[PDB]
Each structure stands twice: as C-alpha cells, then as structure tokens.
Length: 97
Image (cartoon, rainbow, N blue to C red; front, side, top):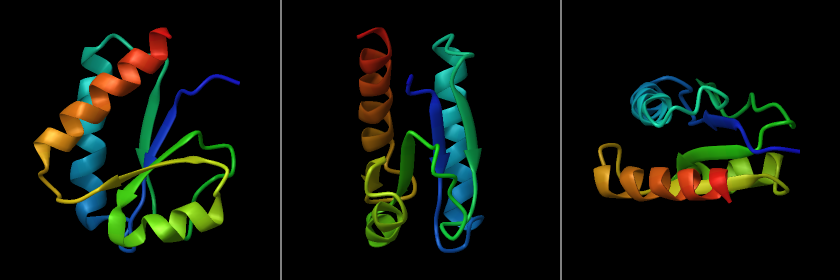
C-alpha cells in the first residue's frame, strides 16, 4: 500500500483540471519520482484505488464523499502557486518518509 497515485478532479473534468494536473505532474517528474503517476478526470469518475485526490475546495466535499477514505487536498485558486509549491514539498517529504 504505497501512495503513488495523484488525480485531479473537478465538475468539468477539463477546465481547471488540465492546468492543475500539468503543473503537479511536472514537479513530480522533476523530483525524479517516475514511480508516481498523474492523471485527471471528472469527479463523477474517480477510481476507488486512488490514494490522493486534488480538487477545488468548492468540490472537495464531493470527492471526499465518493471516497472519504481517500486523501483529499483542497485548492483555493487555479494559479495558487504557493499552495501548489507547499503541497509538492509535502508529498516529497511523505515519499521518503
């Protein structure tokens, strides 16, 4: 049971979904974590095997519901680089640990 799956979901499964996925994906690849996979999909579609779910706070309630047993991270803004940076550092820390 290793956390390696990160998926971004929103009500459109596309709009903000695309940018969030791309940025996170790039950082993960840069960190040499080829073992971690990144994809995006609509909220209505989230595999129960997902370990990490990243969505906008406005829709985090929904994702939690589908899988309240999963790990959810809420965003505030689409280009909130500060939040993205913090989250990335954290995941890296959790990866080693």
